[PDB]
Length: 176
Length: 176
Image 1 (tube, each protein chain N blue to C red):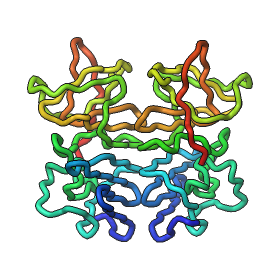
Image 2: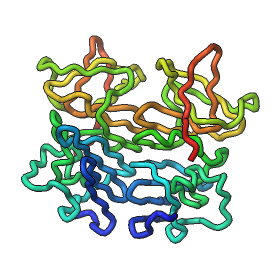
Image 3: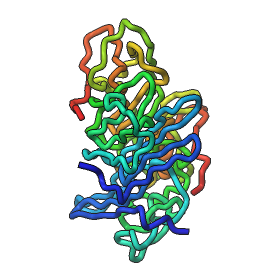
Image 4: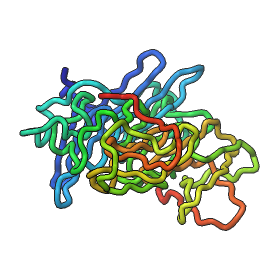
């Protein structure tokens, strides 16, 4: 059911909007459009964010919400970024998750319709610890959706690794 | 003055203690001793954490508090880790800060009294982007205190870089 309304602070002041509670800090900004900027997770939890404490919640498509509504992502158009759909297979079992829109260190991302489609989030280091340097997406926007975690950096579902030899990938096992 | 008591959740349940508010998630654990485990910062702020919402707050030395009381670190013996003093010159101007006790990727830390003393936190990549691989501390404990941020990984004040040639260091400019 709903997360408790009593310990939620949601606020927008001009061109910065924040949905927060005791575990989530979800920040969006206006430059020429509203975009999700950063989301910081003290812990990940499974309840629905209440409507009473949600900005811009009219005519919301659940599959557009970056942070899935099933893990208390607000049902808010602030919880969106052009070029990305819901991150249901992000690395939601990791600790110290921060989601932002920047390159994982030592990597690059190219937009091309050659890319494979959305799948589970992949960590930028292989099982043995090699860095995968090149990535693509069909039609995501840049800078790319990334998750920084206590175990490495991961890209959003849209962004797929570009490899030229056999490699073992570490991929998210979660579906949220 | 004090941060607002109204939007604070502080709880301990057996061997896991959490001090949280709308921006901070500060977690400690008991294994054989109580130690700070992780602290996640949606934003960094400057007010004092109220006593009313502080665990284990008797006979507290301010210079022992990992997260300085001046940036709303709780005045709590849960906010401590053997071998470390207050991180007043941690990288507190960065975004998406997570503090935990693990190695920055590709690095190692040795305890030796050869080390230089506590100073400002240093990022593990130089100005030009080279990785500093070797580090020391006089008498910190392992695993080392680290800050993961949207701009790289940084070590706690105690942990100093070990270099064999001229290099430009990126160091914290903050004193909190």
